[PDB]
């Protein structure tokens, strides 16, 4: 299956910077969401879930088609809670209806990362909405109750290696779990993008416990938590080395995350040779806005 990036007609960098800015300004405005976390974390998660349906073997799923807008995918139990990010983006789409759904969802994640003081993530336009029958079945997003071998095998379907997996999981510094969404009991929450995930894994005192939904999770006396799949990154020796690398080098984490996240968001897409180069958007802070 071949999906060729097609630039929304007549649009260029400045058009997408205005979309970025509208997203970033709403992130600042609607600051009360989720006990003052704001929408940054759920938007990152949304961009990952719309991309993480991809299958390298046949190029089904992926961000290209914008299929999260369809009920089969919108109601995937793995996507419980992402409707909040969808609702956030609705007024942005109403204002800028020329943008494709896939480009909007993916740009939401890029904007959220950068506004939360994370790395710059180059981003490319040209995702094209595809029909309802191209929506992938539920069950392609990962389970949380598994070990390192599961995580490694899982991410091979997304063409991700050990370093890319460990770097992408650092997004779990952001936001929190919610029992009613996923059956995991949240710990301390944050809306600033840092390498704290790896520091916490290494430095905290963890105890395996069973939460009120009967699921196992690792809890620290300081009030943080880790899913079994998070904790697997210090149980496996190859993952552990990389966790230590990122805990000790903020800049290296930022660079590796940026590459892996752009790749995730672009998997499945064929970019023509005359396609525009990737866009690097300015933050509101950089613009004096
Ligand atoms: C093995 C891989 C992964 C598993 C099993 C996993 C599972 C989870 C679970 C169970 C939650 C809690 C959801 C809730 O209760 O609201 C969560 C939250 C989150 N995940 Fe992951 N995840 C994985 C990988 C990733 C990746 C690769 C990214 C991004 C690069 C990411 C970004 C997030 C964000 C930003 C949140 C917080 C959402 C919020 O605060 O609303 N996750 N994830
Ligand atoms: C500290 N915030 C946080 N920890 C998580 C673990 C798993 C999923 C999301 C998370 N957000």
Image (cartoon, helix red, strand yellow):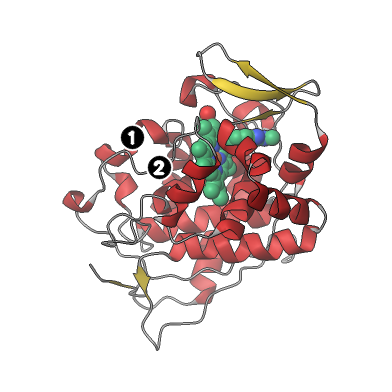
In the depicted view, which residue is nearer to us: 209 or 263?
209
| Label 1 secondary element | loop
Residue at image coords 79%, 50%: 247
137 horizontally vs 126: left or right: left
Residue 281 x %, y %: 61, 68
Residue 186 visible somewhere in the drawing: no
Residue 236 x %, y %: 63, 44
Disc 1 or disc 2, which is closer to the eye?
Answer: 2
Question: Which residue bears the numbered disc 2?
Answer: 141
Count numbered badges in the picture.
2
The outermost residue toward the top is: 212
Q: Which quadrant would the N terminus be assigned to in this image?
A: bottom left
Mark 2: give few (<14), some (14-19) or many (20+) Cα within 10 Å.
Answer: some
Q: Which quadrant would the C terminus be assigned to in this image?
A: bottom right
Q: Residue 87's mark?
A: none
Q: Does the residue labelled 2 lie within 8 Å of ligand 1?
A: yes
Instruction: Tell me whether the residue at label 1 lies in contact with that at label 2, contact meaning CB atoms closer than 8 angstroms.
Output: yes
Mark 1: give few (<14), some (14-19) or many (20+) Cα within 10 Å.
Answer: some
Q: Earlier in the sequence, mark 1 or mark 2?
A: 1
Q: Quadrant of ligand 2?
A: top right
Question: Which residue bears the numbered disc 1?
Answer: 76
| Label 2 secondary element | loop
In the depicted view, which residue is nearer to us: 133 or 16?
133
């Amino acid at each position: 299956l071949v999906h060729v990036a097609s630039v929304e007609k007549g649009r260029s960098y400045e058009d997408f910077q205005k979309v970025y800015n509208a997203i970033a300004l709403k992130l600042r405005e609607d600051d009360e969401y989720d006990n003052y976390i704001g929408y940054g974390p759920v938007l990152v998660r949304l961009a990952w879930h719309i991309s993480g349906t991809w299958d390298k073997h046949d190029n089904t799923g992926g961000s290209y088609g914008g299929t999260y807008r369809f009920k089969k995918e919108f109601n995937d139990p793995s996507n419980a809670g992402l409707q909040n990010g969808f609702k956030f983006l609705e007024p942005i789409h109403k204002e800028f209806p020329w943008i494709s759904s896939g480009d909007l969802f993916s740009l939401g994640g890029v904007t959220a990362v950068q506004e939360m003081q994370g790395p710059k993530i180059p981003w490319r336009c040209g995702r094209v909405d595809t029909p309802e029958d191209t929506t992938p079945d539920n069950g392609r997003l990962p389970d949380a109750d598994k070990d390192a071998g599961y995580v490694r095998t899982f991410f091979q379907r997304l063409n991700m290696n050990d370093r890319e997996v460990v770097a992408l999981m650092g997004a779990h510094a952001l936001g929190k779990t919610h029992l009613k969404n996923s059956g995991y009991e949240g710990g301390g929450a944050n809306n600033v993008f840092t390498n704290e995930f790896y520091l916490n894994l290494l430095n905290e005192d963890w105890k395996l416990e069973k939460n009120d939904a009967n699921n196992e999770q690792w809890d620290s006396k300081s009030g943080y938590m880790m899913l079994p799949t998070d904790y697997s990154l210090i149980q496996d020796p190859k993952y552990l080395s990389i966790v230590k690398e990122y805990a000790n080098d903020q800049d290296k984490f930022f660079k590796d995350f940026s590459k892996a996240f752009e790749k995730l968001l672009e998997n499945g897409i064929t970019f023509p040779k005359d396609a525009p180069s990737p866009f690097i958007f300015k933050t509101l802070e950089e613009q004096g806005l």
